[PDB]
Length: 50
RNA sequence: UACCUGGUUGAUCCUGCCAGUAGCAUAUGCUUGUCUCAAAGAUUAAGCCAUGCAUGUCUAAGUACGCACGGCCGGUACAGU
Image (tube, rainbow, N blue to C red; front, side):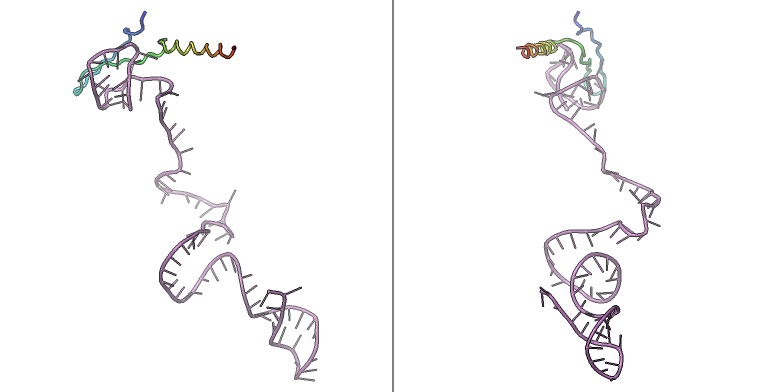
């Protein structure tokens, strides 16, 4: 399942500005950037053996 | 700049020390217009200390749900300060 969309949201209300909602940055999500760092980590091992 | 002078006797020649003469660095007295440098609670007590200051620190790159401030609307991890 997708871990996004199920994340809890916090509503903001005050007399001045418009309503808003907040949610946190997610800390173990395995995005494409995490996978890209894992690929270079093993490309450096191959270069040293050559 | 490798230098001496007064003082023992009625007078002389010596020994020998006292006093004078020049510099240096601590205190102290009288006196003082301009201008460039600049030592300064070591000496006695490593004695006793009111008050203030004398050591802090963030980048594109460890952790941002602070309505704290904010955008054109939306969290697509999640904007931005």
